[PDB]
Length: 640
Ligand SMILES: *C(=O)[C@@H](NC(=O)Cc1ccccc1)[C@@H]1N[C@@H](C(=O)O)C(C)(C)S1
Image (cartoon, rainbow, N blue to C red; front, side, top):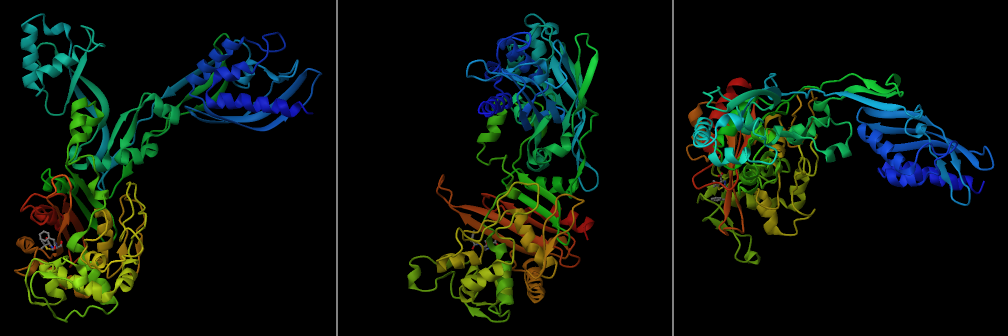
């Protein structure tokens, strides 16, 4: 029995080499090719495993219940159960047999064909048939398509039917001007190594009406992924790309001929959208007659996925950004339905999934405005909109008297001389400032003084009631919002700067809409929701209902008062409660400071909608407030 455990070592090493993909090392562990030993030579074992297991994409061989006994003086039979993963799913409970051999001191395996699959007999063969699964669709809250599959018109040229000289140059220029293409692009496409003169060289996926086709230009219909909104929802939806051999090596249940989501919801929901491949993996005898069916099941097309997004609101929010750096989040704050998740600038997902140029992708990747960023999921300093939270906390703990009038002289203020040359600044030199005036003019000095009077302890008690440090249950990659880098400010300056939303605060636009939902639910925070069929989740008693009834009327004056920072929104004539903001960041590139514009707004009458828009590294005189009129009209009209 001292050699039985040595044989179990070799059997465990044999299945480990098969599991590791090292078919040569597993073939070295066999004995001699005889009549009652190995049924094939060593190099022939490498080929049989590499051909069969490679055809079925066998990966992850796991064994169980190993029993090594004694049959003769030189024969030690063994048996075990095993399972493996193939391109058609998991192949379970496979009963393997065989024998072992040990002549001198080394123990080897008597290789037999049944060590590839249980029922193999000599010249038996393996067949695999597969059928691709159609990818599921991504639809909005009203069934409108966001990521679907349709017929695409592919433009291409046959180098033979172009010409020989001069006529070929003229026909290239005719196609170049008829479809907005570079003459260097056509000549570089038809001059690649794969191009034959009679081949169809694809050029561009045209989306509009088909123009007049010059000589050599033909258009073929191909089926592929299509995004009706395009740039307007590229960061959220994402794109699909060709599946590589490395993707198959990681997950053999993928379709080697299909597409895989590379970013956005296409990647986050890739398993539900891609479905399962159908087909049959069978063993045949030498005659090709089906012997045993190992795996067989029919194709299951991918599921559709309905989002809370409004396709009309998504396009309106994105176009309102005018192609500048920024983002916009629109919700129904009583339920959390994310109506829009726009990010700008953006990339073309249709061009991305239909083959993109190396320089076109380089332009996206090296654009300093970085269109690949999902800005609705990137943490920012919230700015002056965060004063709503600081005021609500000060009202709940009794620190802020809504009618107490602070006397503030000038535009700069500091606690005492220990602050050095640093001072909190404001923009409006208003002498008599209470809570309402502080919100109308957005007074940092008022909030900084109220935050310092409140103290870090009471401030964090109110802050910890929100969603700082929480992972939102959303299919979007994001980091939790943070109050500061550490659990303590350890600085009166940092405490005051946090008071008006300008410390180490990092809150992405989606998390901001979650925190700000308390002003539309009487102090109840409603978590955002992207999947339509999801259940509404909320947190009770985040802030007091009294604070809501005090701040929201003041937020109406931010729009209605003639000196309110959002007074331009009064032109709409709709019930609006808003709060603006402008944060300052230090971008060491140009060294001159950069500014982020912010806007929070919702309907205080029906609580039907709520939006949080922002501009990153805004241009002078540009703001989110001057861009929200069109989106506010649509949300007020359709969401009450
Ligand atoms: C909140 O964001 C506040 N911002 C500042 O104090 C910084 C700042 C940035 C640019 C110019 C001047 C001051 C206040 N709220 C913003 C706003 O609501 O847009 C103001 C610019 C009114 S100051």
